[PDB]
Image (cartoon, rainbow, N blue to C red; front, side, top):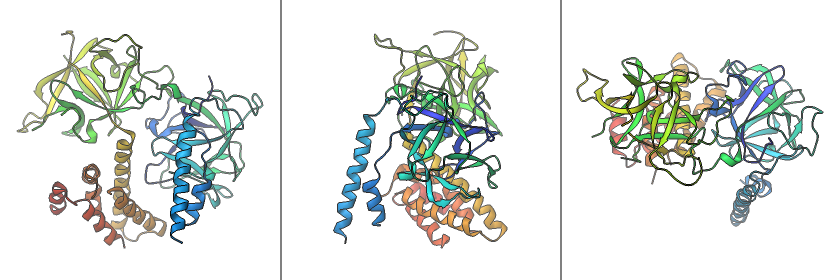
Length: 486
């Protein structure tokens, strides 16, 4: 089993500091390792943040020129040169999908969640470790994104194919100090340890999530974020807190691809013997659905049985089989946008809609119970949600945490310098985010509590804050009516 350009994998630091490289979100650009967060047998709950796609060595020559030049006609020439170079990479790298990576090849590491390249900077010192260079996530990447993939043990050599599970050294082409998992811990995030660049003996185990072969856009696969649309009820399956506990329900309305809240998003896991695996869903596959907003798992438990939200995904009671509504003469793969019914594997029962509200005393109930039946004699659409759409949500959520944190420390008193810069850039990024502006992102401003946090912070940053608020309500009346009601 070999490593392929296009494979999605997690990298597991071994040695003195054991753990998977993950990140601290979408706003913060540091790479960390959380030793107590999860190991090979028991990967971290937030595992989607651990996945990297193996990519080829991008061309940065034309882009380096433009960045460096940041006449006027000169900019056009250089920008067109850079555009053509970014297109070259998309084209050439595509022809490299599914080729075997050989030891000594130069590779890049695209962090899936944030869509950024892990990148060393020769010219910048690590934030924490004494004599080490700095390692960040960069959207476009650059020459600092190039790693030689080298064998940690004499068991394999330069020129050899890289085997899945091999422990490798990831050595920058220019800084030339291997990637390193430090014993240095972050103060702001006690769980995490700094990943930096220095002469050390860190080894990284390539742990295959998904083969390039399975990462097709027209099939349902491990990691896919989906909405579950009950066909005849015309309602999305959502989870949310009511009366200080979590509930699974169908949301009343008054819609098959209508917009909804994040509380209706689900990440599909396809059960695998290996707990770090996922992969393409087949009809004869077993599935789990992790609620994206809370990390809770969909399940069925006695009340006969009703759909509920368990806090963890290691039990049998959270496993569902998918049952097709038609039959084809092709292969066993589940297509995207499939209409399915759900069979709860532990109880041999079928997911069923009801008319029993959860909010009893609450006039105008929007929470309908979903149960299961032993009897055979409906379907759900597995509505796919795009990675961009999920990133958007993750960014909004992280931006929400920062302003929350900083409003707390702002209420205590003085604001630190390396902290005041953090809060200001975010607002410039938020302006750039919310942009004739974008409707679906204006919603995220409100829904994910960016706006509520801006107002919190108010008690320069101020000018920038209002600029967000203004763009957040441009041609949007519901946001206008919200902003005023404070």
